[PDB]
Every structure is written in structure tokens, then in C-alpha cells.
Image (cartoon, rainbow, N blue to C red):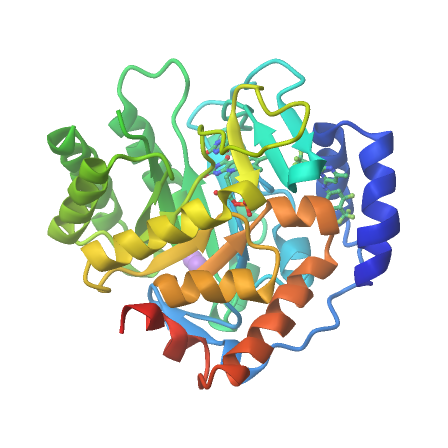
Amino acid sequence: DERFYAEHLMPTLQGLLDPESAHRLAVRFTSLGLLPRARFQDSDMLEVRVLGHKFRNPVGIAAGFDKHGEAVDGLYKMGFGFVEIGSVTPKPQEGNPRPRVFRLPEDQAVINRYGFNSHGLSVVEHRLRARQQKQAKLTEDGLPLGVNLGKNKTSVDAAEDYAEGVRVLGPLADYLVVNVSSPGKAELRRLLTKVLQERDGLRRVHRPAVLVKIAPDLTSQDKEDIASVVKELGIDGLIVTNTTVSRPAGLQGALRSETGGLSGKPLRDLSTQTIREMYALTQGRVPIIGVGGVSSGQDALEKIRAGASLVQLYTALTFWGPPVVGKVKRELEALLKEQGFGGVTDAIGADHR
Ligand SMILES: Cc1cc2nc3c(=O)[nH]c(=O)nc-3n(C[C@H](O)[C@H](O)[C@H](O)COP(=O)(O)O)c2cc1C
Ligand SMILES: Cc1cc(Nc2cc(F)c(C(F)(F)F)c(F)c2)n2nc(C(F)(F)F)nc2n1
Ligand SMILES: O=C(O)c1cc(=O)[nH]c(=O)[nH]1
Ligand code: NA
Ligand code: NA
């Protein structure tokens, strides 16, 4: 229940546990199915067909919650229309020293500097294999799986790390994600060409879509360059956005000046505006998964109207708990009807017209 979690459980956990420990508890409870199944039965208005797949609803769990593929089934039970795991790196790596995750409760925000802690591709591969046919059925039933691919800290050849990820986890995924960072266009083209070649080499029923995930912190020129390369190469979609290294004016949390990526409410509109720009630069031809500061149906609809076909959230779950998933869905449905839309699909990019 919505007020309970929001007003009692999540504030209690906030006071008892550091954020990373609270996250690990969440992963364990979700994976053990200890959480009651979601009440909200998805309506037809929420169904989206994009990336070669049906999505029963457009609200996904963003990368970073289930870094290692431990909680996929429990995430679907929570009501998410799709799950993205990762980021997964080729070799296991520990990530940064702890503490490396900080709450900014006053801002409805988090700052993290995990540093791509990962069990690595082989461990994750075996985890996914344990439920590969279960996932095939879930995907057919409108509940797809994405895999976000990272690179190891010490790697000398980033494109090869990504290529390894494609080869190892691509066969287990409906879509793959590669994160790109600003500080060039020829290097992005080269990387993505390699990734796409590896994807194209997989057998058809094991051949995923490939998306690029971007930061909110790109220059205008960087965005132009990404739009150009993604259209040229036929990248299947964009994930817009990762966390920000900016610190918007007005942050109140004591921990605002910690190094890392900022998520949650302070990111929201910077993300929506990035979606809007990318959608325009790509002429609406490139599906966008919109991410950053979604806590309500309004938040989701703003991203859809700006050009997102699907949305994800993470940070809101850490503040409001599982009920937030059904809240966003229910509010989105209500807003679509109020604004005269037949369904999600009809609202995609509606601001641009
Ligand atoms: C604790 C934490 C860890 C994250 N780890 C990853 C990651 O491994 N890979 C990735 O692509 N994005 C990662 N992200 C970014 C999220 O996927 C998402 O892009 C961002 O947090 C904005 O959404 P939100 O405001 O709903 O959290 C992480 C975010 C948080 C809060
Ligand atoms: C209070 C709190 C809660 C939490 N995640 C979380 C999220 C959850 F959904 C639950 C659940 F579902 F089990 F109830 C849970 F126990 C914990 N995180 N996750 C973080 C982190 F590290 F991801 F930022 N901080 C948190 N703080
Ligand atoms: O530090 C990480 O692992 C991580 C954090 C984040 O915000 N985004 C990401 O892509 N990785
Ligand atoms: Na299969
Ligand atoms: Na198979």
C-alpha cells in the first residue's frame, strides 16, 4: 500500500540502513518473491509495440537495480512491463570502495558512484540460462528483458568489451544497451559498427535489438553527432538518460557534493528535455526509452509526449517502494484518458505536433 510504504516502511529503512545495504535487502526480498504480487491489472491502453516486441505496459526498471540478474522474476511480479539488468562487465569487478551510494532525501534524489561493480558476464550468463525458456514465454506474453553492457575499468579496448557482452548475453536478451559518454564521432561510429556486426552474427531467434544509453550532460554538438551516427548505422533505439554529473542549483541534501551520478527528481526535466531533443534530431524514427526522475503518471506522460515510447524508473522505488509501479501506471492511464489519447502509442511524441 501506497501511504504505508511511503510514510512508514521506506522512512524506517532509510533510518536503519545505509543506501547500499537497503538496496541489497531489496534485491534479496524481490528475488525471494517475498513481496506481495502487484494488484494493478494492466489495461490495453498501456500496451506498446516497439523494438520488435510487445510491452504489456510501458514502465520498466532501469539498469542498476538488478546489476547481476538476480531479481528478474520478482521485478515482473512487482508490475514492471520490462526489466533491464546490468550493467554487466566482461570480467567480475568490485567497483569503488564503500560508501559509494548517498541519499538526498530532501531532494528526492540519490548520488551514486558504484563504478560498475559486476559479477561479470559468465556468472550472469548462467543465471539467465537457468530461466531462459521461462523468459522466452514472458517475452512472448509482453514482458521483455534488456541487458545493459559495460566495460571493465582496466580494459584497453572498450569496443571489444562491448563485443564480448553482445556475444555472451545477446543470445539471452531482447535488447542490449551500450552506454556512451561525451568527451569523437568517428570513434563512436567505429564502436557501434563493431557492436552491430557482433549482434548481426547471432542466430535470428537469439538476435537482440541494440540501444545506446546517453547522459544528460552532452553538449549540443555531441547530441547532433549521436543522432547522426544512430541514424546512419540503424541503431534500434536510445535510452535517455543516465544520471547527471551536474548539480542543479537548489539541491539541499547534505551529501550534494559527493562525486557521482545524480538521479531522481532533480534529473527529471533535464532528462525529458534530452528526450525531446533526441526525438527531434532523429525525426521521431528512433525509439526512445525515457528515464530520469519518474515518480508519477505525469512524469511518465511528459516523457512519452516528448518522444519516449517506454519509460524506466529506479530512484523513485527507493523512496516509495513497490507501490510506485502501480501508482505510475494507474496515473498514466488516467491522464491518457483525460487528454484524449487512445493509448500510450497515440501519445508518443505528441508534443512535437
Ligand atoms: C544506484 C544506481 C545505480 C545505477 N547503476 C546503473 C548501471 O549499472 N547502468 C546504467 O546504465 N545505469 C545505471 N543507473 C542509472 C539508471 O538506470 C537511470 O538511468 C537513472 O538513475 C535515472 O533514473 P531514475 O531517476 O528513475 O533513477 C544507476 C542509477 C542508480 C540510482
Ligand atoms: C530506504 C532505501 C530503500 C532502498 N531500496 C529498496 C527498495 C525496495 F523496493 C525495497 C522493498 F521492495 F523491499 F521494500 C527495499 F527494502 C529497499 N534503497 N536503495 C537505495 C540505493 F542505494 F539504491 F540508492 N537507497 C535506498 N534506501
Ligand atoms: O556507477 C555505476 O555503476 C553506474 C552509475 C550510474 O549512475 N550509471 C551507470 O551507468 N553506472
Ligand atoms: Na531461446
Ligand atoms: Na533457445
Residue 342: percent from left, percent from top? 44, 86
Marker count (numbered): 0
Image location of residue 146, percent across then percent down:
45, 51
Q: Which residue is at 58% across, 53% downward?
A: 131
Q: From the image, which quarter does the N terminus lie in?
A: bottom right
Q: Residue at x 65, y 42 (%)?
A: 108
Q: For the point 42% across and 27% down, which residue is it?
A: 90
Residue 190 relative to residue 313: left or right: left
Quadrant of the frame with the C terminus: bottom left
Q: x and y percent of residue 246 in the render? A: 44, 29
Residue that extends furthest to the front in the rendered view of this protein: 250
Pick the front one: 257 or 27: 257
Camera-nearest residue between 316 and 209: 316
Q: Is residue 46 left or right of residue 192?
A: right
- The answer to which quarter of the image holds residue 222 is top left
Q: Is residue 126 visible?
A: no
Residue 14 point in image, percent of width and height: 80, 36
In depth, the one of 272 and 186 nearer the eye is 272
Residue visible at 19% across and 62% down in the picture: 283
Viewer-closest of 54 and 131? 54
Q: Answer whether residue 234 is visible to the viewer in this image.
A: yes
Q: Quadrant of residue 25?
A: top right
